Each structure stands twice: as structure tokens, then as C-alpha cells.
Image (tube, rainbow, N blue to C red):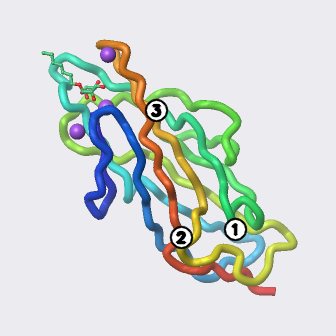
Amino acid sequence: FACKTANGTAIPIGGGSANVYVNLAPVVNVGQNLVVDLSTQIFCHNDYPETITDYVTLQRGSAYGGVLSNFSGTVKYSGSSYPFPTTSETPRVVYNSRTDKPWPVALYLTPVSSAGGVAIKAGSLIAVLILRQTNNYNSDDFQFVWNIYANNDVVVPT
Ligand SMILES: CCCCCCCO[C@H]1O[C@H](CO)[C@@H](O)[C@H](O)[C@@H]1O
Ligand code: NA
Ligand code: NA
Ligand code: NA
């Protein structure tokens, strides 16, 4: 089991960490959503699906910088929505193919009522999402840590 981003940055067997750089809607008004869809950015596969079933959860999702201060949100994982920052580990998604498939996570953020101006700065860390992988074969229990970075500023009109 291993993962890679849309630009080919990989995290190999055993876990580790990688940066994910995201383009963000440049203008978001109070009452509107900023959607950060990681299903187009993070992909994983099972290396031995003939014998092993891999189990993948969103173990934890934390907010940083402008997302922590200026937005409220939820995280959608494999069809269900949860609070973001997260309060617990999600149920598991099965990875049973050697063909890469997306990690089905997206953040649904909305500016807080008093947000205004440059609500997210270009180059800043916005979130850390931990993918936890286990299996039905041995004791492997690994973390694939995804550091989500903004490619651009996001302005909330005042
Ligand atoms: C004849 C025994 C072969 C043994 C192969 C194990 C390969 O293990 C890797 O691939 C497995 C399948 O993705 C993962 O469950 C495991 O954590 C690790 O990433
Ligand atoms: Na690998
Ligand atoms: Na692995
Ligand atoms: Na093991």
C-alpha cells in the first residue's frame, strides 16, 4: 500500500508525509463555500490485492493559519460528512486494487461572519490530513500525513 499526489510526489510502503499544493477559489463571500477537493490530488493503491485487503481511514484532520481562524467547516469522507477540525477517526474505506484510486476526502469551508480581507495567504499551511492504513494480514498500522498548502491568497470581500 502506497500513495501519490497528482504531481507524482509519493509516500511509499510504511507511510510518511508529503505536501499537497492546492489552487483555491480567489474570492469567497460570507455565505459561500470554499471547497478543497483532495480526491483529485491524492491517490493510493493496494500492492497485494490477491491476498490482502487494505483499510484506510481519515484518522484526523486539523486546521491551520487562515482556515483555523477565518473559516468553519466540515470534512466529507467517502460519502459522509464530519466536523472539521475532526473529533474522531472515520470508518474505513477498503482498497482492494493495484490500480490507483482517489482518497475520497474534501473540505467544505465557509468564511466566519467577521472574516474579511486576505483570509488565506498564498503558500500557507491550511490543513493536515492523516490517512491511516491497516490490513487483514499483519500488524501494519501506518500514517500517510498530507500537509495541504494554499497556492494563492483567498479574499473575503468586506
Ligand atoms: C508472500 C508474502 C508477501 C507479502 C507482501 C506484503 C506487502 O505489504 C505492503 O502491501 C500491503 C498491500 O497493500 C499492505 O497491506 C502492507 O501494509 C504493505 O504496504
Ligand atoms: Na512503496
Ligand atoms: Na503501506
Ligand atoms: Na506487520
Given the current orientation, which residue lies at the most extreme right position? Answer: 114
Q: Mark 2 points at which residue?
A: 150
Q: Where is residue 129 in the image (x, y as percent from the top left)?
A: 53, 47
Give the amino acid at mark 2. Ala
Foreground of the two, 86 or 125: 125
Residue type, label 3: Arg
144, 34: nearer the viewer: 144
Q: Residue 114's quadrant in the figure?
A: bottom right
Mark 1 residue type: Gly
- Residue indicated by mark 3: 132
- Residue at 79%, 80% in the rendered image: 116
- Corner quadrant of residue 90: top right
Residue 35, given in percent of the width and then of the height, sits at: 57, 63
Q: Name the residue under label 1.
A: 66
Extreme bottom residue here? 158
In space, the residues marked 1 and 2 are separated at their CA atoms by: 10 Å
Q: Is mark 3 on a helix, strand or loop?
A: strand
- Residue found 70% across the figure and 36% down from its top: 87
The C terminus: image quadrant: bottom right
- Nearer the N terminus, badge 1 or badge 2? 1
Disc 1, disc 2: CB below 8 Å?
yes
